[PDB]
Image (cartoon, rainbow, N blue to C red; front, top):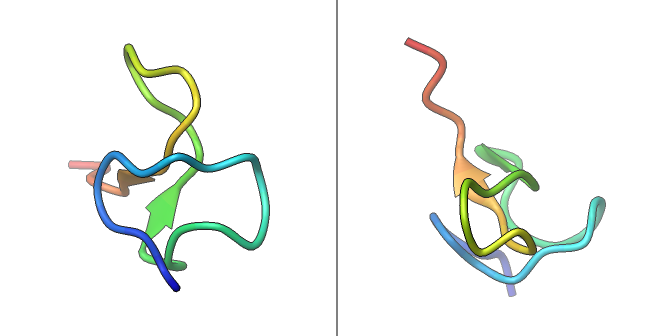
Length: 36
């Protein structure tokens, strides 16, 4: 079950490859990768 922006994540095998496991508040999720 992939995960989208802001989704409880640990480090590997959590949200979809289109995001990363680093939040700016929840501190425990996967945020979409938007490296402008």
